[PDB]
């Protein structure tokens, strides 16, 4: 039977057969403390905080990795599990140097939420005050390694979701550090596409977006609005956090979709930075080298006088934006394509759109769809980039390409 | 005479954990009507008396502030660690990644328009430093850890209210922060 | 494509004494299109921001709803329509964008007649699979 | 600098298009060059089309790889259970304070290197202090000088 | 041959130690005043992102966590190179005025009010805030209310009271909605009454002890403050060092300060001694705090505090009041000023605005932010590299400039209250009150 | 002395700037066939940001000249 029935903390739970105990747990309602399970990334069993006990079996097993078997009694909260989880959290606090007073993520840290939940009013284990490096060479991301629980959710999100496999582990045992290429700094790395998906995966404030530090906290958000990035065609799904009329943090939903929330630099770094730009909000006028504040009547008069003396003799055009909605573009068509009938209206990328829709048009005559979805370049065997630079055109397509050609054995051949 | 006998002090604190104690504005009148404040940065006593709830903010960074912490522990029955500086080591512990000689040398000799040409390194009569900043649960057994920078006024009031009723409180999860 | 894209390229290779350019100043703009805009002799930009590459080639610089104070639908090449949501509401009062288009229609001898959003019906449809022929050019 | 770009690009040739083989592909550049320079790992990552981070992780994960030039005479002391119960720790710490170098690093001019190993096999003649050529069966505290000057 | 120690110096912030080395005859050879704590906020920060500094630097003190917040914010705003927005200016000034009010309320009513009211020979059990609540139930409550007013402004703006986060590098995180603006403004007729009653009380204390309190550690030194065009500004402005008898000596932009201020490191204390470099240590040493500001300002901007500022100025031989105990009086003027400055910021439509932040790339290598904390001028000077990583910080803090004034004041008050033996407790309270006149945050001094 | 003014090809002042911060506006493209670099207005890109200098560009960019008798012939140039 696929639909199995278990008992977590007395509460009965329902799940698919292959689901782990954590899956059947998060499916119904029940809470199990986790620090290294990122919905999406394959269950990595490193934090050992999700340990649950089966009735009769005196040992404890991780709920993230152990599967659910056809009927069984799982106990998540009792004295011994609370003691062991508090000891694990205290080991993490004692090994690495964790100062919450100045951490960008003090309110979001999942090691801090767990510590407060388990009433960690101490450290118990001797504080090893060793010197882990603070890699803030990258002007966009900062990696403060003395907050690194070592959950590999950043190696896994840059190995299986982004593909530009920049982060891996350095040494063994206690000396294990998360490093960029050849143990270099993130700025010195050639293979970082500066995506930030490493900052969306890090639960423990090691990797932080610098420009929006202390503001892009999810606990201090005024609102959380789900939408779509309008910068490229991939149209990544986003979970924009709004704090006093500005977007402070853009984390990408869609950890179940093939992309995996790895929004690009333009989406995790230009979308929140654009909510803090100059914002005219009053009709200006040139005057020579420096604008002057004008009224709407004055500005539209000086802009329509120049639109009548230049429409009699044809001499008039319009370059609208293709990042505009269909409502706005339909409005612009109402004025420009129909009312005054200008044949000189374009869309700031009209060459690309008209080339694409005049090259694809033969096949529309023949009666086929001459394009597929980008998530199908993940299971392909040979990828051919013809005249493309997908890092500057649609970076999730480039990430798909990288995941394919590294973790799924493809081959790349360019005709550019 | 029948009032309780708290007595605070700071060791390597920035004074915020007491500033939060004085953030008990109108309720400080009621607390003073319930407890008499022996040795503390508010009263002008110089030697700690025998007390009931000995409070300590700030970690251990010098030698004098280990001695006063040991004194406070020796002279009370419940000790309250105020702040992350006394509970987790705090911000003082940021000097643990460089030696104390280097700490005193970059902040007194090469410190961006200081004008001593002899390398004075001021350890003449003042307590020198400790080689590493530590929490107060390294030389003092603590009974009520109160974490935060600073512990909110509500949390301080709760800890005092529960220690004056005759029990050793553990700060609940709904009102504890590390800030 | 269904509303603005012109079937012939005109930018750069035609004079265009007047140019109303709407630029949600987000994506880096092709630098050839920017030059073409700079040699126009009157450029009315309705950009929301005062970013560098647009306040230089502009004579009027009107405001706009700035991608997070408006909502829309975004019909794409792959068919289905998405949804952009109003993340944070507008602060000031641009009071419309139809007002600007109307005041352009006014004293120009033309009307407006607001139409409905043209239903995006995926012009490229897959009625054939694994059965195509090549196209001679 | 050009001596380290084709020797590594030739030992990778019999592994192209074969799954696996980074543990051996390195044990060969180690035996040839004595160590694994950054150029070596860079060319391995280029040729195998394996990530540089993964190559560095495997190169620093296993003990017998050395990313820095190892010395011309290794001083492998045995910190095995049999030697340690016999007191090999004393011999280890005295070769430590005698060469003056840190636990697992090379001398300042590439003459010696201390590499605490597992059982070298002479668990009868304990402790053993191999000086890169042959076993050394007894190695009391005083017999460490008469060999460390000889092999240099 | 032998010495007296007043360790720990109480009713001040931080750790202090007054030593009074006497002779064989029992007379004061010399006194010094050590600060016995040091944390190292100039060596912590090497490696940290500069944006982390407005959250690291408030932990130098809890009586003034917003002063260090705002100095670090101005330093990082000069690192970015932002304008900054007028609404951000006025909100930062509102937070700074709230901090002025709360710190001066704590400095007068909690720490220095026992000596001012009950006299330096009062019993030790009554000389505290507790005995003040007991015997004077209304004045302690009024001081608590003034401190609560300041900290309610700070909490409204930046979440927490102590160590708030309200000012990002580049601007301000949160504005004021009209409800809380009206709430803060509805208590100002009462808080101004509290401040004026305290002004009258301290003016009657100083007028009662006529000439003795006018020579109680009163040495003629220089007066550093911040000034607008000619006014008393506490958030921005140029630095003005008035000579000990009225002449403006080297008014300078706070940016180029390394060419004017130096720090001498004396062995016996962790506190450096900043001084005006052209005159040299110990002849360039100046004063800071409320006294030095009112001495350096030619006029104040607020209406009702201007009257009592004028009454302060017609007390001191062409505007230069040298008396140490008048540091209490001046303090409350500041408080008064602060309160009446709040009323001006809450009457402007820009504190409630929504354009608070300005972002920028192109991080400069140096950023110097100088504000006027309640105990004196505060200088944050960060040097960052291309990556925005802190390379070298320098904080010249308030109590540092007053260290020499405090040392010389303890010397003068010791050298007038010597006894060969028996070393009484009231003279100890006077030796502590010279320090409590400046009410020093020794945690700031020793970052 | 004075500020740098780049007039667009049909009259509009494009990016008048202080000569100090010039690295954010002017770039140089190195073509293989000549030792002369090609400076250009960086925002428009090579070869669309390339501008003119010399007497023509000055008189085209200046709205007026200061001298009395050369102003007449400058006006004759402008019409
Ligand atoms: S990472 Fe989390 S637990 Fe660690 S210091 Fe930061 S907030 Fe605290
Ligand atoms: S920014 Fe993207 S590519 Fe770079 S390390 Fe992070 S996840 Fe990987
Ligand atoms: S950097 Fe963060 S996400 Fe990566 S392993 Fe460390 S704690 Fe986990
Ligand atoms: S790839 Fe980047 S720009 Fe494109 S939709 Fe996704 S997040 Fe937005
Ligand atoms: S724990 Fe925080 S509030 Fe308390 S003294 Fe330390 S820095 Fe200040
Ligand atoms: N005022 C004050 Fe506190 C000090 N010194 C700061 O800054
Ligand atoms: S949470 Fe189950 S092991 Fe990491
Ligand atoms: S015990 Fe050292 S050789 Fe095996
Ligand atoms: Ni202070």
Image: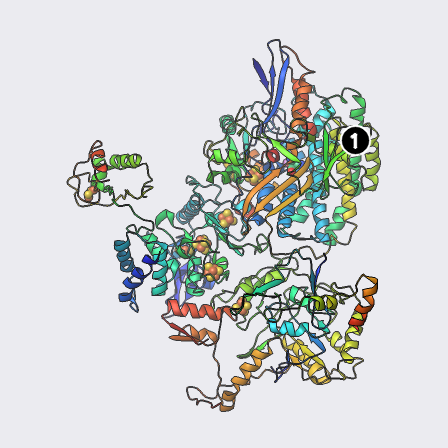
Q: Residue at x 51, y 86 (%)?
A: C125
Question: Relative to E312, does residue E24 appear above or below in the rendering?
Answer: above
Task: Decide if ligand 6 comes within 8 Å of the CB at mark 1.
Answer: no
Q: In this rendered view, identify the residue nearer to me: E337 or F24.
A: F24
Query: How packed is label 1: few (under 14 Cα within 10 Å), some, or many (20 or more)?
Result: some
Question: Relative to D105, does residue B136 appear above or below in the rendering?
Answer: above
Q: Residue at x 31, y 61 (%)?
A: D6
Q: How many marks?
A: 1
User: Chain for mark 1?
Assistant: E
Q: Position of residue A266 (x, y in %)?
A: 55, 65
Q: Quadrant of the N terminus of chain A?
A: bottom left
Q: Can the viewer see residue A33 in this picture? A: no
Q: In this rendered view, identify the residue nearer to me: E308 or D147.
A: D147
Q: Position of residue D80 (x, y in %)?
A: 23, 42
Q: Quadrant of residue F69?
A: bottom right
Quarter of the image where ligand 3 sits: bottom left
Q: Position of residue E302 (x, y in %)?
A: 81, 42
Q: In this rendered view, identify the residue nearer to me: A69 or A231.
A: A231
Question: Relative to E438, does residue E186 appear above or below in the rendering?
Answer: below
Q: Mark 1: which secondary structure? A: loop
The residue pinned by badge 1 equals E246
> Is residue A250 rendered to the left or right of residue D52?
right
């Amino acid at each position: 039977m696929k639909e199995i029935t278990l008992t977590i903390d007395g509460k009965v739970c329902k799940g698919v057969q292959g689901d782990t105990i954590l899956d059947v747990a998060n499916k119904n309602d029940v809470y199990i403390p986790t620090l290294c399970y990122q919905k999406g990334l394959t269950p990595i069993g490193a934090c050992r905080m999700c340990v649950v006990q089966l009735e009769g079996n005196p040992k404890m097993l991780p709920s993230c990795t152990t599967p659910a078997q056809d009927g069984m009694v799982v106990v998540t909260k009792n004295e011994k599990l609370k003691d062991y989880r508090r000891q694990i959290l205290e080991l993490l606090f004692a090994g690495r140097n964790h100062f919450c007073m100045y951490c960008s993520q003090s309110g979001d840290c999942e090691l801090q939420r767990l510590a407060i939940e388990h009433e960690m009013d101490s450290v118990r284990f001797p504080y090893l005050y060793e010197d882990f490096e603070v890699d803030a060479t990258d002007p966009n991301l900062m990696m403060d390694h003395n907050r690194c629980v070592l959950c590999q959710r950043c190696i896994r999100t840059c190995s299986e979701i982004v593909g530009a496999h920049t982060l891996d582990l350095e040494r063994r045992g206690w000396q294990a550090k998360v490093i960029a290429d050849l143990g270099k700094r993130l700025r010195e790395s050639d293979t970082c596409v500066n995506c930030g998906a490493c900052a969306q995966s890090c639960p423990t404030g090691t990797i932080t977006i610098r420009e929006f530090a202390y503001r892009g906290r999810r606990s201090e958000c005024d609102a959380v609005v789900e939408s779509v990035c309008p910068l490229c065609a991939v149209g990544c799904k986003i979970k924009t956090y709004v704090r006093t009329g500005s977007i402070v943090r853009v984390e990408g939903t869609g950890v179940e979709e093939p992309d995996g929330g790895q929004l690009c630099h333009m989406g995790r770094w230009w979308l929140p930075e654009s909510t803090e730009r100059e914002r005219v909000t009053v009709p200006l006028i040139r005057e020579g080298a420096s604008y002057r504040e004008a009224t709407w009547e004055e500005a539209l008069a000086l802009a329509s006088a120049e639109f009548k003396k230049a429409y009699d003799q044809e001499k008039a055009g319009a370059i609208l934006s293709s990042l505009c909605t269909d409502e706005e573009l339909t409005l612009f068509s109402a004025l420009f394509r129909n009312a005054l009938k200008m044949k000189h209206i374009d869309t700031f990328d009209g060459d690309i759109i008209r080339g694409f829709f005049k090259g694809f048009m033969p096949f529309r005559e023949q009666g086929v769809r001459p394009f597929t979805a980008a998530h199908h370049i993940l299971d392909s065997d040979l990828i051919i980039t013809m005249f493309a630079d997908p890092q500057k055109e649609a970076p999730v397509v480039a990430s798909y390409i990288r995941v394919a050609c590294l973790h799924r054995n493809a081959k790349l051949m360019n005709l550019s | 005479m029948a009032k309780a006998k708290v007595a605070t002090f700071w060791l390597e604190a920035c004074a915020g954990c007491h500033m939060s104690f004085l953030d008990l504005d109108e309720r400080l009148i009621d607390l003073f009507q319930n407890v008499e404040i022996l040795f503390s940065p508010i009263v002008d006593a110089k030697d700690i008396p025998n007390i009931d709830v000995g409070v300590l903010s700030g970690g251990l960074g010098n030698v004098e502030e280990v001695e006063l912490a040991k004194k406070m522990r020796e002279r009370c029955k419940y000790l309250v660690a105020w702040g992350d500086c006394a509970v987790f080591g705090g911000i003082n512990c940021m000097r643990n990644f460089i030696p104390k000689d280097v700490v005193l040398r970059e902040g007194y000799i090469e410190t961006a328009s200081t004008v001593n040409p002899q390398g004075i390194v001021p350890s003449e009569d003042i307590p020198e430093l400790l080689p590493r900043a530590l929490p107060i649960d390294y030389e003092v057994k603590v009974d009520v850890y109160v974490p935060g920078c600073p512990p909110d006024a509500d949390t301080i009031y709760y800890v005092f209210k529960e220690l004056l009723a005759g029990r050793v409180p553990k700060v609940p999860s709904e009102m504890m922060r590390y800030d | 494509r269904n509303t603005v894209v012109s079937e012939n390229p005109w930018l750069g290779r035609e004079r265009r004494d007047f140019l109303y350019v709407f630029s949600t100043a987000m994506v880096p703009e092709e630098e050839e299109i920017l030059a073409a805009i700079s040699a126009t002799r009157f450029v009315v930009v309705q950009t929301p921001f005062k970013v560098r590459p647009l306040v230089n080639l502009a004579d009027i610089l009107l405001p706009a709803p700035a991608w997070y104070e408006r909502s829309g639908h975004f019909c794409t090449i792959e068919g289905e329509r998405r949804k952009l949501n109003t993340i944070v509401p507008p602060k000031g009062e641009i009071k419309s964008l139809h007002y600007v288009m109307d005041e352009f229609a006014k004293k120009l001898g033309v009307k407006l007649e607001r139409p409905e959003v043209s239903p995006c019906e995926e012009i490229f449809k897959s009625q054939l699979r694994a059965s195509e022929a090549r196209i001679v050019t | 600098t050009v001596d380290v770009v084709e020797k590594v690009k030739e030992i990778v040739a019999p592994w192209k298009g074969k799954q696996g083989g980074l543990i051996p592909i390195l044990q060969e550049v180690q035996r040839e060059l004595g160590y694994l320079p950054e150029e070596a790992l860079l060319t391995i990552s280029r040729e195998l089309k394996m990530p540089k981070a993964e190559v560095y992780g495997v190169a620093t994960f296993y003990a017998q790889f050395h990313l820095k030039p190892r010395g011309r005479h290794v001083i492998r002391v045995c910190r095995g259970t049999a030697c340690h119960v016999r007191g090999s720790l004393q011999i280890l710490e005295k070769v430590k304070q005698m060469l003056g170098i840190e636990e697992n690093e090379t001398t300042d001019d590439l003459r010696f290197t201390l590499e605490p190993v597992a059982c070298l096999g002479a668990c009868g003649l304990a402790p053993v202090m191999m000086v890169d050529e042959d076993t050394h069966g007894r190695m009391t505290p005083d017999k460490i000088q008469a060999i460390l000057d000889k092999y240099q | 041959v032998f010495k007296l120690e007043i360790n720990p110096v109480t009713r001040i912030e931080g750790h202090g130690k007054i030593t009074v080395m006497l002779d064989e005859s029992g007379h004061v050879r010399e006194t010094r005043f050590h600060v016995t704590q040091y944390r190292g906020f100039e060596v912590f920060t090497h490696g940290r992102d500069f944006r982390e500094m407005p959250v690291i630097t408030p932990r130098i003190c809890g009586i003034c966590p917003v002063s260090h917040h705002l100095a670090s914010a101005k330093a990082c705003d000069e690192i970015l190179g932002v304008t900054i927005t007028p609404a951000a200016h006025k909100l930062r000034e509102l937070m700074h005025m709230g901090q002025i009010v709360q710190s001066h309320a704590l400095s007068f009513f909690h720490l220095s009010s026992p000596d001012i009211l009950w006299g330096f020979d009062a019993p030790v059990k009554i000389r505290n805030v507790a005995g003040l609540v007991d015997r004077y139930p209304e004045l302690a409550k009024k001081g608590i209310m003034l401190r609560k007013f300041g900290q309610e402004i700070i909490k409204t703006l930046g979440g927490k009271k102590i160590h708030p986060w309200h000012s990002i590098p580049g601007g301000v995180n949160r504005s004021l909605t009209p409800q809380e603006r009206d709430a803060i403004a509805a208590q100002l007729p009462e808080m101004k009454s509290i401040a004026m009653e305290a002004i009258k009380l301290i003016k009657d204390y100083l007028q009662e002890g006529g000439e003795e309190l006018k020579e109680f550690a009163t040495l003629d030194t220089a007066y550093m403050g911040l000034v607008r065009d000619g006014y008393l500004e506490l958030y921005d402005g140029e630095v003005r060092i008035k000579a000990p008898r009225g002449r403006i000596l080297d008014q300078f932009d706070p940016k180029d300060y390394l060419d004017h201020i130096g720090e001498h490191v004396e062995p016996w204390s962790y506190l450096k001694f900043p001084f005006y470099k052209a005159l040299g240590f110990p002849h360039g040493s100046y004063r800071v705090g409320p006294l030095a500001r009112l001495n350096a300002a030619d006029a104040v901007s607020t209406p009702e505090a201007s009257k009592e500022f004028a009454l302060y100025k017609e007390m001191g031989e062409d505007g230069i009041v040298p008396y140490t105990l008048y540091y209490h009086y001046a303090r409350l003027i500041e408080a008064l000023y602060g309160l009446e400055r709040i009323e001006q910021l809450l009457a402007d439509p820009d504190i409630t605005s929504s354009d608070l932040r300005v972002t920028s790339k192109e991080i400069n290598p140096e950023g110097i932010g100088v504000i006027e904390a309640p105990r004196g001028t505060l200088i944050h000077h960060y040097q960052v590299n291309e990556s925005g990583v802190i390379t070298k910080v320098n904080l010249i803090v308030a109590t540092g400039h007053n260290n020499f004034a405090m040392n010389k004041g303890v010397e003068m008050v010791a050298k007038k209250y010597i006894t060969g033996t028996n070393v009484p407790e009231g003279v100890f309270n006077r030796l502590e009150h010279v320090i409590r006149a400046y009410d020093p945050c020794l945690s700031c001094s020793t970052h």
